[PDB]
Image (tube, rainbow over the protein chains, first blue to last red):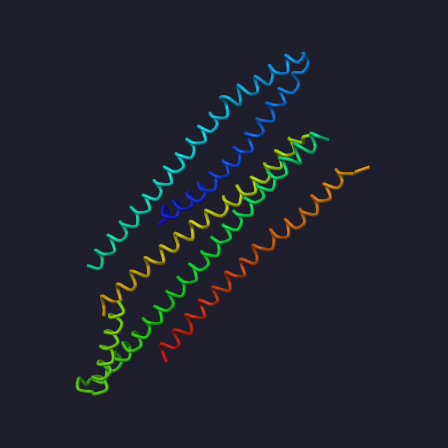
Length: 108
Length: 97
Length: 54
Length: 54
């Protein structure tokens, strides 16, 4: 009965902290956007060439490769979260079937 | 003023509202969990107390027949009738299970 | 013009609220679940013993 | 011209008041609720025992 409660207790915390890390991620992405376009902002020390080559870096490096990698890492987080929740749900079934199996035999 | 009215006024403040909304939703959900646990505890307590009462009802007739033993009469109609009472009591309790 | 430091620290406090409350809540919820199962088992034993006597 | 430091520190003290009092209050309220349920249970047992004797 102790670990029976420990399971649910960890499960609820897992479900909460998944969305809390999701919120952290969305707060992080637009921060990185602002930082990227701000690093690309002060590249006006050159002429019009230095402008477009700075926005080329901002739009090809971060906008081209970094953000989908962030999405991919997020996807793996989602998948692992789902898998572990399934493991929890399976262990629930296990415990309850064991308890029923015992009580029936007690009655018999 | 373009920066002040496009960055903060355009994106930051609705993000603050969105974070606030999630806070509200989680607050409501956890309060609902609390309210559910309340129901759980109180239903469990009532379920126990009712069974306690049902047991003590049988215990009453049991002790009654026990002191009806000590007349040293096996042919006492009081004793026979109290036994009939206890039999039907046990039948009605077992039928409930 | 973009107080992003203050913004992030605000978000930190906001998140830290919910962290603390989830942390405090779920433990006690699990304690409740344990006590519920324990009372269930006691109930089963008591009723079983009574029925077997009867 | 905008004493915002002093403003915020005032708000800090004001909030800290209510934090401390909520903290002190709710614990004792829960203690009361516990004692109420305990007295209820004692009452139930005593009355039950009397009735079963009678």
